[PDB]
Length: 175
Length: 175
Image 1 (cartoon, chains in turn orange, red):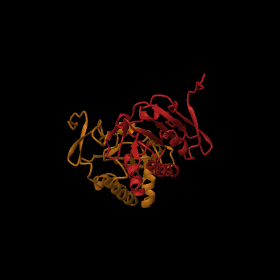
Image 2 (tube, chains in turn purple, red):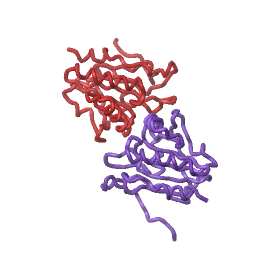
Image 3 (spheres, helix red, strand yellow):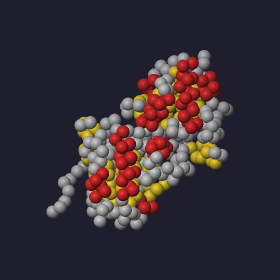
Image 4 (tube, one colour):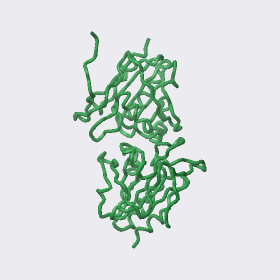
């Protein structure tokens, strides 16, 4: 019927060259997997700590790189025009690097979370770059979860140097 | 005879509060363990790539923190006055964060290496912070290796907010 074709791994591109991304990004209409990530104060943050709220996961390789830096600036602004939603900027950057960027840029709407102590999130959310120079970093992706911990939108950006589809991510939140 | 007392873990301090650091830092007169770390160009760097040269390992929690930032600035200057030696600045910061600091500061003598894809180095070199908010980051430490891959100096800084003993590290290199 409306099933998905079998995948063993995902393939994105870095300046046109193929990159293997582990497993599969969560699909719309499926249960969001539990996660623990590290906040600005070095405390542990779970998915369950955002119950009753909608969640935008803006996953990227490094906040210290241009395209990822633009996505964080965009999502910070888009957070003002969305109802009952938390915007989480997720990467393998240490909490200190993430806070330094947000601090210097005055971006206070988004919530920065590090996978530095939680490499498993990259595996479970299907964003772990498996090969090439960017191995161990997160692929560029967007995962939108509803109030009920159900995935409502998912995007694994085909080319890593391209910004994510903001409008498509925000469209599922509008009722 | 001249043996060391049995340890199961090490204890450093963060603003006076005890912090458990895994295993044991390599001791002087012992073989240096192999390692693979990630350079500025995202390439893999081994210990064997510095054969015939003496090695200063300046291990710290984050280049995006003050005390660690000072140690990198100090070691960059001290590298000019030392014979046949490579100075390696090692941390869990991503290569992008390490290069951004070195670039902005104009520090070109030191060699930055990331443990981000190689969590095992922190275990083998006895610098892995096991508990508290800083878990997963490296403890502040100095490991000096000779040309023959033998450890000649070792220091696990007792208090994490204190700078390492530069003079003692550089003293073993002088013949």
